[PDB]
Image (tube, helix red, strand yellow):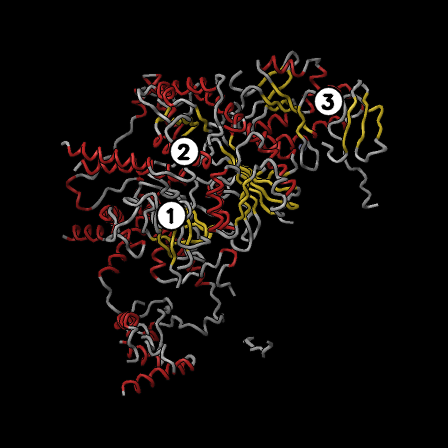
Amino acid sequence: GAKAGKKVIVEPHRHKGVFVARGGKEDLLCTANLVPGESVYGEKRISVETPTKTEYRIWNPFRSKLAAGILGGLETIYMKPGSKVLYLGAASGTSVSHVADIVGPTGAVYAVEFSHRSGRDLINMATRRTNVIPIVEDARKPMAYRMLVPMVDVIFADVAQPDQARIVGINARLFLKQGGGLLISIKASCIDSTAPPEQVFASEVQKLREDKFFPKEQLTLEPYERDHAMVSCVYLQKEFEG
Amino acid sequence: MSSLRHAIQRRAHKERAQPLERQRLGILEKKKDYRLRARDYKKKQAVLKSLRQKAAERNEDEFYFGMMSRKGPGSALTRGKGFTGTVDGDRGNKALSVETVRLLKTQD
Amino acid sequence: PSSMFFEHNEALVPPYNVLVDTNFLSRTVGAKLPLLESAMDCLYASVNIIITSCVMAELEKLGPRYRVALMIARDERWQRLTCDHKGTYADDCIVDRVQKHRIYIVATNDRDLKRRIRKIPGVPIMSVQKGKYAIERLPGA
Amino acid sequence: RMFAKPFLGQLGNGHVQGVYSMCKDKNSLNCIASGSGDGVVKVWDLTTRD
Amino acid sequence: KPQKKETYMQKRAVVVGREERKLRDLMQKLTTIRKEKIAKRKAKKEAQ
Amino acid sequence: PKVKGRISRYLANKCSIASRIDNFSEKPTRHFGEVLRQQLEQRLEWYAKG
Amino acid sequence: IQILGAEKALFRALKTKHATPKYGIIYHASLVGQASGPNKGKIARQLAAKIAL
Amino acid sequence: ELSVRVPQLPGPPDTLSDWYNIPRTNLTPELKRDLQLLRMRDVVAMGKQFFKKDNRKDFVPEYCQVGTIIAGATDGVSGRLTRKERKRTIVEEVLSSDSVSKYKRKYHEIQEHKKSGRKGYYKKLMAARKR
Amino acid sequence: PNRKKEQRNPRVKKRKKYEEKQKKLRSVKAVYKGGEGPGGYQGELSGIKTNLVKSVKL
Amino acid sequence: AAWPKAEDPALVQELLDCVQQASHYRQLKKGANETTKSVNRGTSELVILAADTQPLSIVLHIPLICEEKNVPYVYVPSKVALGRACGVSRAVIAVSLTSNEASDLNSKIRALRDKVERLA
Ligand SMILES: [Zn+2]
């Protein structure tokens, strides 16, 4: 396929911070690498010889639900370079590394994980990248890292818990600005393993509107993950920023 | 109707051809080829009629500014043998100053 | 949308979510038919029956002559989708919600709404027919 | 007279029958209760009117 | 009118090598096949 | 041949075993690797039997 | 001696009828570093000739 | 501690600050051939793999950068081009690839179809009439 | 009038029509069709378009 | 170190019965490396690890990718019983039972993973 050594060109995608790398017989998605020359989880990276220190990392959509959503055609993702992002469910920091690279050096990414060994991997990734800070605590109890997390602009949620809506509800009630963007990744098989997927997504969107967001988009990222859906909402407003 | 005919009713009729003693003259013109010819010739006659109307209703005292920046068709008398009624179009080549020719010739 | 095979809505499974329109609600309490019981007898299946704030607002905008229908509408055991929009126009609220998610069965009786949701694919329509309910475009009943 | 828009909200789904009695908590600030006509009483907190 | 005398620019034009002529022939072939393909696609879509 | 591929796959298996042991211990030990090297030498004698 | 070191750009420009590079290692020499643009080119020629001498 | 300043007072942006400063396209003719290829890649993989028909008026973007895939640490025996195939330009890779005979064959078929009856056929008919 | 063997065997007709109607389904929406292949990620094999959003606007 | 240890009362035996059913249905993968590859490819619907293995680091490395990819993983304390349930005639320590689009085994999987998600 996209063999190592093929020449591609790199154009900027519509979102602020993601690039699309097109070339030859395969077009793929990439983000600007923050630390050059050192891959995180063995991903392919693209080198550009500017007329060195600039390189891009190829984003695996089958492995990261956010990349799956952006190829699925989200209207927006709310995370411009420089915008603080609270990431819930930061298991081993792959997608978190990508989000930190999108946000860049002036912002921050607050990776909240829970399992200790995935926490060790996340500690390694945060020693490498200087704009992500790691927090190993149970996301159901935000009174633990209320001393660490300031008012972020985006909340990513990648937890599959039956209490997913309540988890994002309390974390947004404590750490999200007025009109605060969030993305949630909903897995129907874990939310209600008996129910059909469209009904599960409708139930979760209604639970979020009870928990005071306003849903603006919902897509079923079907050619990359079965029975998933990415739901984009805004906290306590209708527009995103102000 | 359409279910009230047999397949032998629906069977297509074959198209005959030019006789072999006359194949050298070209293809035998049937109805479809004839319609192609009629459309082409009627279109060309339509455009020629519109041009004749224009050349008749030409005002002899018009003045644009392309008339200051082009080389008009003239006549057979002025243009000589190489005279088509069209105005000569700019090929894009031009007259080059001596300095630039020195530079190009140094490169050569 | 997910779970949609050429205008066959695979997503609807018992328990059926059935949306109520004001017209269907008024005419069923007129025709003296228990709402959940008759709907369960019509679909042979468990239903949860939902009523929006727009439908409740139209029943309340109608005068006190519909106090009995208002009480039956506010029967407590039924879910209530609160709406986030302005005009409180129940037809556009129902059609917008159905176009968004497409899981519910619309229960209505007026021919304008009936045609307006027959235009979109894959939504069954329940309507009163003076003896019982009648479901229109559901493949499993 | 342009900006007189007095109506704020409606405390949840309301009752089945009519609201025939109600009373506030003179000690607190957001505790209210309403007793309807069918014989159900409800206690609402005014911060969350859902 | 098609010019007949060779201009100085046409004379001083450089000859082009094997790799570049191969790439030019390849681009000609790919562009032609693209044109015929897009014409057939537009004609079928017009029929539908 | 085939012996090179066979012993190479076998050695890769034993290498991954050593890696997971030495990583997921806290302060690892040596005798598991000694036992594995003994198994490698015994497979070396087994392929010498040929 | 002027275009020592710029051989790749020189021969590509000459075989493509481009404009040849103005200087080579004489750039990172000191004395041409005080000039700017066209005076830098003229100092480059003059320094090449005197270096040959 | 406090020095005299130097007065340095004597269109489209050069670097997109919001995308970490991607340079503007230096439109070399090799880059133009590469961009023709990238708009034309529905024809390159001849029939075996189709792509989403992205066709604008101008196929050059306003911001690009030519790059190369470095390496996958999980795949390095077949997911890595050899030295004799690492070509500098994408179109050089395409010409070094296979099916160039297939392109030539299809091109000859289209050439025959387009020279079907245009003028050589009419010259032939005129000679057969005059003989 | 003449008919086909697909018309002569009523099971095969509802096999051939279903497979054809399954093929049309992949042309409008998308089917999961397995995750990443065993070879690894070889790029989004058929194009990436920038100006296309495909989310259900709530 | 195996904190999602399955308890004695019949949850372990429901797990073993489901594993045997999946082995008959051929929707099952045995072995440490095959579990690792199925989890990496993302076909794994659930994964069970033995807790009485020789040193626990193997069935400790499987939960790392398991937690990275968010699959339900449990520990059953008997590798010989795991082998006798898979039907191997040798001791397995890692079983990843995958997902299809149509069975009743999928319903049994849904019930079982609901129980183990309650366990975690
Ligand atoms: Zn509404």
Q: Amino acid at mark 1?
A: Lys
Horizontal relation, residue C121 to residue A57: left or right:
right
Residue beneath the point at 36% across and 26% down? J29
Q: Amino acid at mark 2?
A: Ile
Q: Which secondary structure lies at badge 3?
A: loop
Q: Is residue A238 above or below residue I8?
A: below
Q: Nearer the viewer, residue H26 or G49?
A: G49
Q: Quadrant of ligand 1?
A: top right
Q: Amino acid at mark 3?
A: Arg
Residue C22 rendering spot, x and y as whole percentages: 69, 24
Report, in whole angstroms, how far the alpha carbon at label 1 lies from the one at label 3.
Answer: 60 Å
Query: Which label number is shown at residue C74?
Result: 3
Q: Which secondary structure lies at badge 1?
A: loop
Residue H101 rendering spot, x and y as whole percentages: 22, 47
Tag 3 subunit: C
Residue beneath the point at 53% across and 37% down? A114
Query: Which label number is shown at residue A44?
Result: 1
Tag 1 subunit: A
Tag 2 subunit: J
Report, in whole angstroms, how far the alpha carbon at label 2 lies from the one at label 3.
Answer: 54 Å
Callouts 2 and 3 in the same chain: no
Question: Is disc 2 in contact with disc 3, using a CB cutoff of under 8 Å?
Answer: no
User: Does the beta carbon of the residue at mark 2 sit less than 8 Å from ligand 1?
Assistant: no
Q: Say few, some or many: other residues with alpha carbon within 10 Å of mark 3 (under 14 / 14 to 19 / 20 or more).
A: some
